Amino acid sequence: KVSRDKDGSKVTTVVATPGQGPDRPQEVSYTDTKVIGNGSFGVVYQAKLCDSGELVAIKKVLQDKRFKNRELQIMRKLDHCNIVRLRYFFYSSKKDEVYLNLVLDYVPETVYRVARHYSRAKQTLPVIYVKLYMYQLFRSLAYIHSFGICHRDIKPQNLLLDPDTAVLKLCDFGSAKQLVRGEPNVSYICSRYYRAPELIFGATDYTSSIDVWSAGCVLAELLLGQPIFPGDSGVDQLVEIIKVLGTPTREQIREMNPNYTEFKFPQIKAHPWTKVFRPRTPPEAIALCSRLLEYTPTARLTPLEACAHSFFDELRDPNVKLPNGRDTPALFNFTTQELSSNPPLATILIPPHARE
Ligand SMILES: O=C(O)c1ccc2c(c1)nc(Nc1cccc(Cl)c1)c1ccncc12
C-alpha cells in the first residue's frame, strides 16, 4: 500500500485488480476510511474513491494463501444490477498474514433497518415497497441460481437498499456455494428465523430452494412487522413453523431428511394462512407466501416463477411510480441467462410496454 497525506487527509494507494473484465491491475486511491462493520470473518470499511469521488465498501478478510478464495471466485463471475458489485480486489497485511480486500458498492440502507423503523413506529411498510424489494431479491436469486449458486444466508440485513432509487443489492456471498447434486454440503449455513426446515433437520443434500424459503420468511416478516418463525433454538423455530404449516406429513419429512421420519413432532393442524396476517393484507401476497413456505423443497416456487407471481403485477403497470415521485428501477431488462430456468415466462415478466 502507499499512504499519502493530501491536505493532511490520509490517502491510500493500492495496485488493485478489477473484479470484472480482464486481469489488469490498476493504481487506485481512496481516502475517508472508517470502519462500518465487523463480522466473524473480518472488518468492512467505508471509503471515498480519490478520483470518481464515489463511496465504496472495503471488506478485509484473512486469506490463507493455501487455497483459492471461494467468495472471490463467485464474486468475479457475478454481474447483476441487484447484486452488490465487486469493483476491485487486492491483498495487504496480522503479522506474516495476508489479507484479501474486496472493494464493493457502497449502499446506504438495508431492508432490516427499514423494517425496524416501521416496526418501532407501529407502522407497516407500504406494499409497494414490499413488492419492490421482494421482486429484486427474487430476481437476484434467479440470476445466481441459473449458475447453480446458492447464497445460503438470505436475511434482511444482507439486502442493501438505496432509499431514493429503491434499488436492492444482495450482499455477503461468504456463505455462497455452487451446489452440485450428489455432493454433500455443510448444513449449518443460513441465519436464525430464515433457516429452511431441511436445514434445521441438519440435511446435507439440500438444494437452492433453501434461498426461496428464506425469501418467503423475509416477505412474511415485511407483511407481519416481525419474524414469522422466531426462536433461539431449532425446537422453538420448528414449533412456530408447525403452528402455521401444520405438522409435516411422513412424505414431507422424507423430502427434507428421511433420518427424521420416526421422531415425535408437535401434532398441530394447519392454521389457514389468511389468519396469519393482518386483515387488510393483500390476498395475492398471502398466496405468494404460501407458495414459498412449503415443507417439500421441490414444491417451492423458483425465483423466476416468484417474479411472475400475481403479487408483483402492480410493478408491471405502466403508471407505477415510486412514492417519492421517481420512476421505479429497471425491472424488465432480463438477460436470457436470467431466464434460463424458464424462458417462456418472459411473456409475463417483460410487459408489452417494455419491449421494442
Ligand atoms: O460482504 C459483502 O458482500 C458486503 C457488501 C457490501 C456491504 C457490506 C458487505 N457490508 C456493509 N456494512 C456492514 C454492516 C454491518 C456489518 C458488516 Cl460486517 C458490514 C456495507 C455497507 C454499505 N454498503 C455496502 C456494504
Image (cartoon, rainbow, N blue to C red):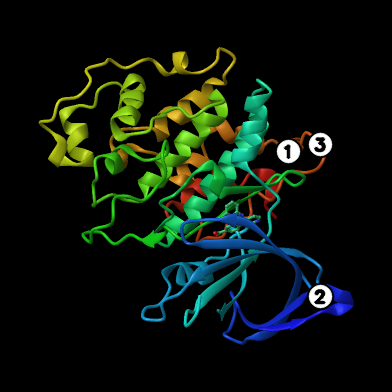
Query: Which disc number belongs to residue 189?
Result: none
Q: Given contact means CB atoms under 8 Å apart, are the residues at marks 2 and 1 in contact? A: no
Distance in Å between CA atoms under marks 2 and 1: 38 Å
Return the residue at label 2: 51
Q: Can you tell which quarter of the image residue 179 is in?
A: bottom left
| Residue 28 horizontal/vertical position (percent) | 71, 80
User: Regarding mark 1 in the picture, which secondary structure is present there?
Assistant: loop
Distance in Å between CA atoms under marks 3 and 1: 17 Å
Query: Which of the two residues, 84 or 282, is positioned nearer the viewer here?
Result: 84
- In the displayed orientation, state which residue is furthest to the right: 7
What's under tag 1, amino acid-wise?
Answer: Pro
Neighbours of disc 2 within 10 Å: few (<14), some (14-19), many (20+): few
First reached walking from the N terminus: tag 2 or tag 1 = 2
Q: Relative to 152, does residue 348 appear above or below in the rendering?
A: above
Given this view, does label 3 or label 1 mark the residue nearer the observer? 3
Neighbours of disc 3 within 10 Å: few (<14), some (14-19), many (20+): few
